[PDB]
Image (tube, rainbow, N blue to C red; front, side, top):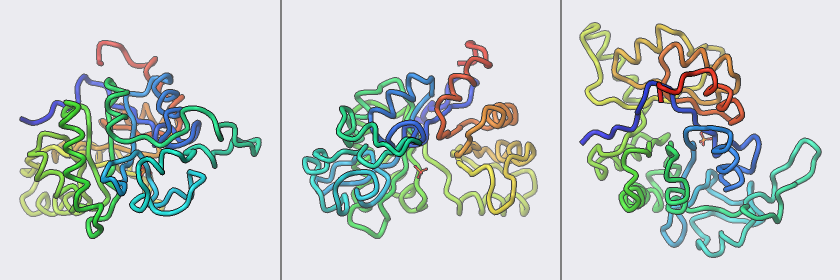
Length: 275
Ligand SMILES: O=P([O-])(O)O
């Protein structure tokens, strides 16, 4: 029943929002470029529309990344799809080279699964649990995963523990889920109480920053401790090849990078038999 999400012996490299540093975030121009650059999958976010259809989108409003205005929850999928999701992407020249071009449109989570059936999906449920969109999003998320037979290649996480709570009750543990911050805090507590005898019963991915308020979280003993706790350690914001090799040798299993170009370089270093 447990999903075999992690296969092989090489850590998965994810492009942050499809590789937002090089191409407009959440657009096909980004997913195509990152996939060409040799990434293992896409880190992404989902928002629910008025049609109750999940779209690949980060902000609650389309103002930052499109030519439109307003919340995604107030727009239809048809209205959202007339917008240019590359309208505000600027290169270092100051130009917007992808404004008005093809493949600059918003995508639904359904079309993302059908179009890239070989990529791993690390998806974030963004809508708050208190909201109306957040109540029905976990179910719609599972239905989309279920309709595309992608139980073993999608990782559903959230900043809110309750969204992971509500997705996991529907998914029956048939889809890998991210670890909440409260669950890790109470994992450390049951460790000190029960000694090293404790481990988490179900493996969950805990994605971390490489640094937080001056505190380095790349300690080899911390990564080893998490693995001994049966907590799968991962890191986002990894934008150098030496840090990628460092986390790979310490035991991290997921890497989210804004720079998908380094993924191809990382893969050349590792052997093909590990995959
Ligand atoms: O997609 P992120 O920016 O919420 O990690």
